[PDB]
Length: 280
Image (cartoon, rainbow, N blue to C red):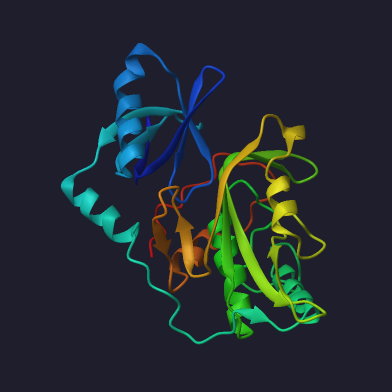
């Protein structure tokens, strides 16, 4: 009766209104487990796995984000997750400019990125699923970075974490973290500034990281607060709260996730469809 969610690493466990909210690596979605006598051991397993950044096997109640069972990971699972979620930092191998020369070029890059939005005739496949804010922010950000790279530029990522909520203007989503590209450019006086580019939240253009994080704590959606943020090299696909990095150097995961979410829009389906198939 339970849905096999597969193996993953829990990265947060946070109590709210009679329910325990669990966050996992990569996915931006919250999962929940009820603090009942019968869930007491599953909850302990999750708490220990969060502490130690170790994998577990997750089973969900059908058609929900509710955890029904947690099973231990094998020594093989432990070995694998250590290889992919790593402190072994490795930077971009291609030579690129880390600073965009002027705001005109920043704006051009913004337009090129927005032109790749799913639902616009200018976009090529796989299009960037900005209109589907439920999950996949990591893939959207890596695809935005690819556009910069196609222009000869690199950038940073900013990962923001917490009890996040955002509105599309018609509906709200909840996230354990969000990520977008943080682009450095020279202003009119030649001073380097940074802006976030994130058409899933700001359709008009680049915005300050302060404004961006504020949009991730939209209290019109309910309770919200930021717990942390971290800037990373652009090549980081996902950063855990323990400062481990996951990479997607050939955009294998990125393209697979974008392809899966291509026709999705709005705040449903939630949970998002399974992208476990994707790999790297």
